[PDB]
Image: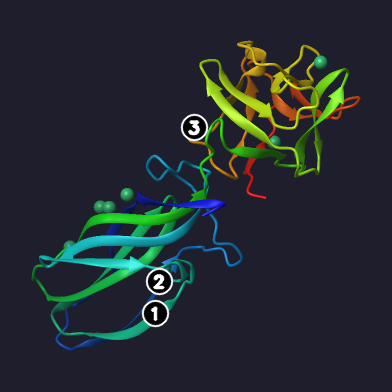
Amino acid sequence: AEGYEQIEVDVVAVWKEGYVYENRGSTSVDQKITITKGMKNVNSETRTVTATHSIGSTISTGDAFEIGSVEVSYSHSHEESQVSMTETEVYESKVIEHTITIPPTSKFTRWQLNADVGGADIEYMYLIDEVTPIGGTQSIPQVITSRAKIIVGRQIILGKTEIRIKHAERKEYMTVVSRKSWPAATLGHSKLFKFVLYEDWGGFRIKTLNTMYSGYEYAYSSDQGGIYFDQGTDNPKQRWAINKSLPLRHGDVVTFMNKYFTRSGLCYDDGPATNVYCLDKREDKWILEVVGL
Ligand SMILES: [Cl-]
Ligand SMILES: [Mg+2]
Ligand code: NA
Ligand code: NA
Ligand code: NA
Ligand code: NA
């Protein structure tokens, strides 16, 4: 799969008390109970969901992911069962309605199973409805295993994966042009200009694969503020700090903070020739885009 990657991740699920009615009378009662299966406040145009909280080690808050297939293992009355919910089921929100006649001196209980895929509250994954006499005992349904397959951006291998660095606000790729007398970063529409990321003891590095002057390839911050590409050195001016934890992924919105100039970070600022600068108290958003075209 070139582009994105599927990962099975452990999700939290729960058996709620979906509806309760207690018929303390001597006559039977009719009740029109209505439920809504599927993901709550689901977006009609896109299937991509942004996380409101983490999903173990793979997902963290803000990460954009896609479902998938939620699978829950549970038990009710000493019998273990497995309920699955396919892609079209989790996104299409169905409304189910049926009458239920509660007998006299009894209680109707509708157990509702819900899953929480990193904020995505999937309502009524399954249903168990039991009638018990007053004052009888119930069988509380217990969840055993809750997992879900999710599709996320493919993993960026440091040193191998060729990428493009696009600005989040302006929506333009980082290109390399000659400023003064060495290669300097600017912003344009060219897709031919790629990069490759590395990580060492000093930090992250932005190597360009389209250098004008051979050897001068690692992105660094000059004293004047501008961005230039220089030869491989331990100099912290050419190392960087990425806000997102490893492993990095395709389509990740990241920010590059210089290791030498701690407060200063990679951003856009229309200068004399170039427009990609590293300025104090500024940290513009950049999207990592993996190449397969
Ligand atoms: Cl030079
Ligand atoms: Mg619980
Ligand atoms: Na798993
Ligand atoms: Na659970
Ligand atoms: Na109870
Ligand atoms: Na920004």
Residue furthest to the left: 136
Numbered label attached to residue 245: 3
* Coloration mode: rainbow
Is residue 280 something one can see in this rendering? Answer: no
Tell me the amino acid under the disc marked 1: Ile
* Disc 1 target residue: 96
Question: Which residue is rendered at x = 17% and y = 89% of the image?
Answer: 27
Q: Amino acid at mark 3?
A: Ser
Q: Of the residues shown, which amino acid type is indicated by label 2?
A: Lys
Mark whose residue sits in front, 3 or 1: 3
User: On screen, 218 above or below 44?
Assistant: above
Disc 2: residue Cβ within 8 A of ligand 4's nearest atom: no
At which x and y percent is residue 190? 80, 43
Q: Where is residue 84 drawn, in percent x and y?
A: 32, 67
Q: Can you say whether 224 is above or below 191 in the image?
A: above
- Of circles 2 and 3, which is in front? 3
Is label 3 in a helix, a strand or a loop?
Answer: loop
Disc 2 secondary structure class: loop
Horizontal and vertical percent for residue 33? 34, 79
Secondary structure found at label 1:
strand
Q: How far is mark 3 from mark 1, CA to CA?
A: 42 Å
Q: Earlier in the sequence, mark 2 or mark 3?
A: 2
Question: Which residue is more in the foreground, 84 or 115?
Answer: 84
Q: Left or right: where does residue 200 sit relative to residue 20? A: right
Q: State the mark number for residue 37.
A: 2
Most distant residue in the right direction: 272
Report if the CB atoms under discs 3 and 1 are less than 8 Å apart: no
Whether residues under marks 1 and 2 lie with C-beta atoms below 8 angstroms apart, the answer is yes
Q: Residue at x 43, y 77 (%)?
A: 95
